[PDB]
Length: 144
Image 1 (tube, helix red, strand yellow):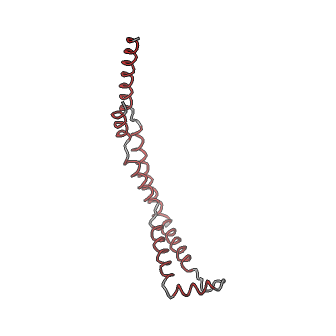
Image 2: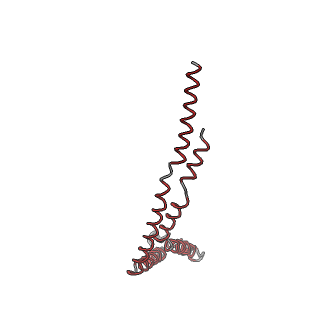
Image 3: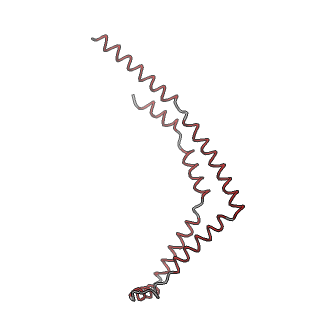
């Protein structure tokens, strides 16, 4: 029984060492990230080329600006529910609608800063930043 246990334990230790080796050597996923980033950059170039040829982003920025201006322009002075007009005017003399318009304009500027190129760049940053090989090395040197 002692011999059987010793043989089995030595075999299990050898299997664990081989498993660590296999973990270390199995890193083919790392190849994918670089290719994904490359294609993302290619498409960033392509998209910016297309926009420069068809005014898509200029028109979209104008659309966003005008939509936020319309949201700003909504007047509650004329609105029904008479108290609405009174509250609106009391706000008018307390620059509260000015604060509402400032918030709307800040949101408008931020949204107009949300660009397809920015999204692609952030996605490429996320893909390239992490390396699976570091995680594999950590796994092979911790669990034992």
